[PDB]
Image (tube, rainbow, N blue to C red):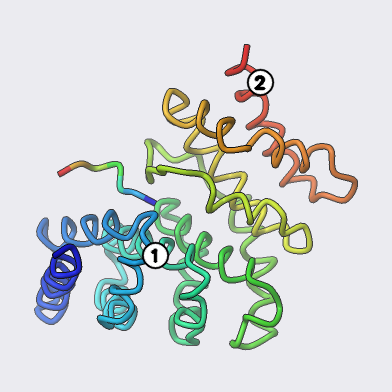
Amino acid sequence: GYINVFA
Amino acid sequence: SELFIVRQLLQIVKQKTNQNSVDTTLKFTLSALWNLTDESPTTCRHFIENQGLELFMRVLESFPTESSIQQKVLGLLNNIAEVQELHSELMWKDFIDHISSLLHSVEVEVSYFAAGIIAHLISRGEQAWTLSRSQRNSLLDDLHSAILKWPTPECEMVAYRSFNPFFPLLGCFTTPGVQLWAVWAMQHVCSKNPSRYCSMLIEEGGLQHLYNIKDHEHTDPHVQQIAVAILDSLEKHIV
């Protein structure tokens, strides 16, 4: 869904 | 303006792939494009209308050894696979044969999205599979057995803002590998980060959809054996 890694 | 961003990030992917350049900018660009398409069919149409699919095949091919690059690409494709209106778009032989191979990837971070793509495409039924009927059935059992070989990821691979995408998969009783992927995926994100998902899995109807699997007459033992493992943490989350 979303990537856990931010930025 | 967000479609400009998608186009621009797609442009960076095109650029990095043309120059066959695995680096933090490409890996970040995929991640960005993976996020922007999450729970965003509209941003998924643009990825598709802007040749993202064919571009991402190029990425998958260009970097067959780059598991992070594969995961983020497949992550996006997992997001396209959640959109029914984009089904016939992924109904592409060279794409599925590749996905189907990454399904057996040892990297669980890679195969998980491979499987999730596969699962979503199988979940659409016998009719919607415009590819080889024999392969769809090969995938049906390859998807199942691939999941059973999977390790517990070391960390959280994927983030979800909702489980609704997984809910229609729970009802693919004719295709247990599809159901297996769904329950494994919830088993993963819940057990990895139960402070995030466990409440929400209830609050969206997970309990019942998970109870209609455990307490279902005909259910694959593994699909049920995961729905059991999830409900134990869910029921522990309730009390």
Other-residue count near label 2 (Cα within 10 Å), few / some / many at <14 / 14–19 / ≥20: few
Q: Position of residue B116 (x, y in %)?
A: 51, 59
Residue at the location (26% across, 57% down)?
A: B36
Other-residue count near label 1 (Cα within 10 Å), few / some / many at <14 / 14–19 / ≥20: some
Discs 1, 2 touching: Cβ within 8 Å? no
Q: Please state if B167 lies on the left or on the right of B35 as rendered.
A: right
* Residue type beneath disc 1: Pro
Which residue is label 1 attached to?
B41
Q: Is residue B30 above or below residue B227?
A: below
Q: Please state if B153 lies on the left or on the right of B136 as rendered.
A: left
Q: Position of residue B100 (x, y in %)?
A: 52, 72
The span from disc 1 to disc 2 (Cα, nearest Å) is 33 Å
Residue at the location (51% across, 26% down)?
A: B199
* Quarter of the image where one finds residue B34: bottom left
Q: Please state which of residues B239 and B20 is positioned toward the viewer in this rendering.
A: B239
Q: Is residue B180 above or below residue B101?
A: above
Please indicate, yes or no, whether residue B21 appears anywhere in the rendered image.
Answer: no
Q: Please state which of residues B42 and B185 is positioned toward the viewer in this rendering.
A: B42
Q: Position of residue B183 (x, y in %)?
A: 62, 44
Parent chain of label 2: B
